[PDB]
């Protein structure tokens, strides 16, 4: 493709290397993507609202294009979240009078949605984020209070996994979440999946989002989350990895490029992280970055609107950053 080696090829015997994509990137960054990633995830085009905007109408155009792109190139595809409190259209939770949908309506609608979406790509998607972010960040709260929990019921996770498993018994079913390394939330997610497994739910993996930064979480904290989750006998996927140069509610907004400090910390940070991933390659089977290159990232608008970020190992011009070289795998 040019000079630099293929990132995914360097991990061909350890774990997949993926990237979140959007159709707009294909006929422009398609060459770069096929070069460095052997796994892709629709950043947004497979979400409920994106593929099922209205009750009786599905819009799979974008998702279909991404899948054609990947499968024709031997690139794997992770399906992103079927059940999530965000990006799910209002119709799903409402009845004809605009009131709340009943438990029965919720169940039949969820069944048809999963059957349509999961069934559509049957045998083509190696892993599905079945339930996303069900655990609360608040210390004294376990289950996030969402319409799924209120309208469908406390068994909404079991239901989702059973339905997904039925739509495609060959796909690996994942429970995906962020802040997965925080000791308190870690134990909640651990107990959740454990209880799901004890209930017979077909959950085959835990997705560690990996929305980290140059200051944390620590190697020790990440290590503990890994061993903790792996002890449930499930595969582990780092699903939305990015290393923000900013912290939580950062007050800095004048940066037009990372500071010399940020660049140096990020490079070392990425080296440490992938060093840890290699150590646990027996538990981690896929590592996906939530983007392709610094020219685009959802962090450019979250949590702060219009604040440019540079979270990847590839810069705004798709050129490798120092971190890239320190991340190359051993194969």
Image: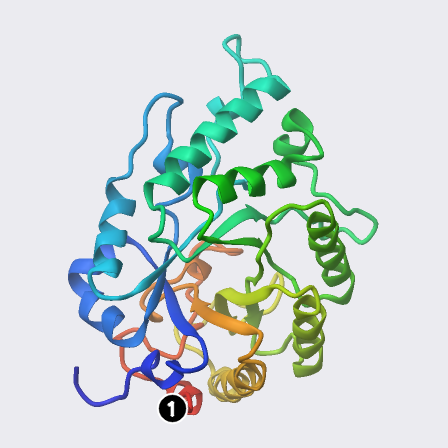
Where does the image place residue 113, in percent across and percent down from the top left?
44, 32
User: Position of 223 compared to 54: left or right?
Assistant: right
Residue 275 position (above or below residue 234) = below
Residue 121 position (above or below residue 319) = above
Where does the image place residue 166, in percent across and percent down from the top left?
49, 40
204 or 248, which lies in front? Answer: 204
163 or 149, which lies in front? Answer: 163
Where does the image place residue 257, in percent across and percent down from the top left?
40, 76
Residue 259 position (above or below residue 77) = below
User: Few, some or many C-alpha atoms within 10 Å of disc 1 (few <14, some 14-19, many ≥20)?
Assistant: some
Residue at 46% across, 85% down: 263
- From the image, tell me which residue sits under label 1: 325
User: Position of 172 compared to 125: left or right?
Assistant: right
Q: Residue at the top extreme? A: 97
- The quadrant in which the N terminus is found is bottom left
Residue 15 position (above or below residue 269) = above
Residue at 57% across, 57% down: 204
For label 1, the SS is helix
Residue at 40% across, 22% down: 55
Residue at 52% across, 85% down: 278
281 or 208, which lies in front? Answer: 281
């Amino acid at each position: 493709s040019t000079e630099i080696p293929s990132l995914s090829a360097s991990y061909a015997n350890s774990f997949k290397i993926g990237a979140a994509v959007h159709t707009r990137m294909l006929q422009t960054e398609g060459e770069f993507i096929a070069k460095h990633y052997n796994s892709v995830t629709a950043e947004n085009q497979m979400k409920f609202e994106e593929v099922h905007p209205r009750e009786h109408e599905y819009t799979f155009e974008a998702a279909d294009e991404i899948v054609d792109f990947a499968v024709a190139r031997g690139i794997g595809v992770r399906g992103h979240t079927l059940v999530w409190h965000n990006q799910t259209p209002a119709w799903m939770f409402e009845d004809a009078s605009g009131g709340t949908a009943s438990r029965e309506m919720m169940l039949s609608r969820l069944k048809q949605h999963i059957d349509t979406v999961v069934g559509r790509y049957k045998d083509q998607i190696y892993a599905w984020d079945v339930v996303n972010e069900a655990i609360e960040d608040k210390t004294d709260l376990i289950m996030r209070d969402t319409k799924w929990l209120r309208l469908l019921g406390e068994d909404y996770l079991v239901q989702a996994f059973n339905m997904a498993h039925e739509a495609d018994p060959n796909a690996l079913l994942f429970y995906n979440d962020y802040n997965e390394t925080d000791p308190v939330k870690r134990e909640k997610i651990y107990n959740l999946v454990r209880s799901l497994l004890d209930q017979g739910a077909p959950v085959h993996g835990i997705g560690m989002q990996g929305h980290w930064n140059i200051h944390g979480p620590s190697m020790d904290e990440i290590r503990q989350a890994i061993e903790r989750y792996a002890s449930l006998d499930v595969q582990l996927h780092v699903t939305e990895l990015d290393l923000s140069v900013f912290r939580h509610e950062d007050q800095r907004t004048d940066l037009t490029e990372p500071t010399a400090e940020m660049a140096e910390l990020q490079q070392k940070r990425y080296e440490d992280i992938f060093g840890l991933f290699r150590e646990y390659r027996s538990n981690i089977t896929s590592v996906t970055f939530w983007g392709v290159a610094d020219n685009y990232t959802w962090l450019d608008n979250f949590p702060v609107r219009g604040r440019k970020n540079w979270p990847f190992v590839f810069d705004t011009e798709l050129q490798p950053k120092d971190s890239f070289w320190r991340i190359i795998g051993q194969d």
